[PDB]
Image (cartoon, coloured by chain):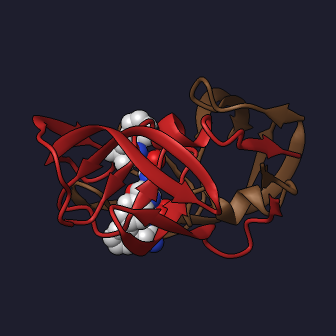
Chain colours: A red, B brown
Amino acid sequence: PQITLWQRPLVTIKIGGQLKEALLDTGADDTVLEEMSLPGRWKPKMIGGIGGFIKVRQYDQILIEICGHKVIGTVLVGPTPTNVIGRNLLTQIGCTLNF
Amino acid sequence: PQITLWQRPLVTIKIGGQLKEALLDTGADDTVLEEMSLPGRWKPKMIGGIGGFIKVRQYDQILIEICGHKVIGTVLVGPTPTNVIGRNLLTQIGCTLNF
Ligand SMILES: CC(C)(C)OC(=O)N[C@@H](Cc1ccccc1)[C@@H](O)CN[C@@H](Cc1ccccc1)C(=O)N[C@@H](CCC(N)=O)C(=O)N[C@@H](Cc1ccccc1)C(N)=O
């Protein structure tokens, strides 16, 4: 739907059998979630933002249900304070900015 | 207008007589620009993101032209790698996410 930005744009996502809240972030190229138990294996990686850099595990081809829309893509798991849905998944569900 | 997320959502802003490029970020509550010469009074402040926290100066009541729309609000100036336009200004220009 159409979501304004008066409040943080938080949505419910279903990933790996679990329900979580995540922030839709147009300023993140990638999607990174707080530490959680995920299946399969990973390739380690480092990402940065405001503040500095962190280490995350990279899981590809993972299924996620965001506001119902099921999408498959890479998800990074690590020490991030909050779960963020990045552009790699946002394009998947046809998300656009408007004004 | 309507902007897809296949590429970073970069726009041109005019602030303090200067032209700069900034990333439209729905995941930032605040707007923070790389070090620049700004006139006026400020209160110091600290903000955080993924790799920890940084110190920035808080300049209030600042004018900015984003994609033509003039808006007035708080801007934070500091060691951010890129300039990001946060929700405090995005609501000013009527920006929404759609899908
Ligand atoms: C996630 C990934 C892929 C590593 O990308 C970024 O971190 N991108 C960030 C910087 C960047 C973008 C593009 C290229 C290079 C670098 C930017 O999108 C910021 N995204 C959010 C992600 C986020 C959100 C919530 C929590 C943790 C992380 C952010 O840090 N936003 C900050 C921006 C600074 C600001 N003050 O607005 C924010 O809103 N911080 C809040 C909330 C907060 C408090 C304390 C700690 C963390 C966050 C604040 N008031 O300080």
Quarter, ligand 1: bottom left
Quadrant housing residue A92: top right
Q: Residue at x 68, y 65 (%)?
A: B88
Q: Residue at x 27, y 46 (%)?
A: A76
Q: Residue A60 location in percent, x, y?
A: 29, 35
Which of the two residues, A71 or A45, is positioned nearer the viewer here?
A71
Say if B18 sits above or below B90 in the image. above
Q: Residue A93 location in percent, x, y?
A: 66, 42
Quadrant housing residue A3: bottom right
Which of the two residues, A90 or B87, is positioned nearer the viewer here?
A90
Q: Residue A33 location in percent, x, y?
A: 31, 59
How many numbered marks have been drawn onto this rendered protein structure?
A: 0
Left-right relation of B26 to A43 = right
Say if B96 sits above or below B14 in the image. below
The answer to whether any part of residue B46 appears in the image is no
Q: Residue at x 73, y 66 (%)?
A: A5
Which of the two residues, B36 or B6, is positioned nearer the viewer here?
B6
Say if B73 sits above or below B26 in the image. below
Q: Residue B5 location in percent, x, y?
A: 64, 32
Which of the two residues, B19 or A41, is positioned nearer the viewer here?
A41
The answer to whether any part of residue A50 appears in the image is yes
Q: Residue at x 53, y 57 (%)?
A: A65
Left-right relation of A81 to A96 = left
The quarter in which the N terminus of chain B is drawn is top right
Left-right relation of B77 to B89 = left
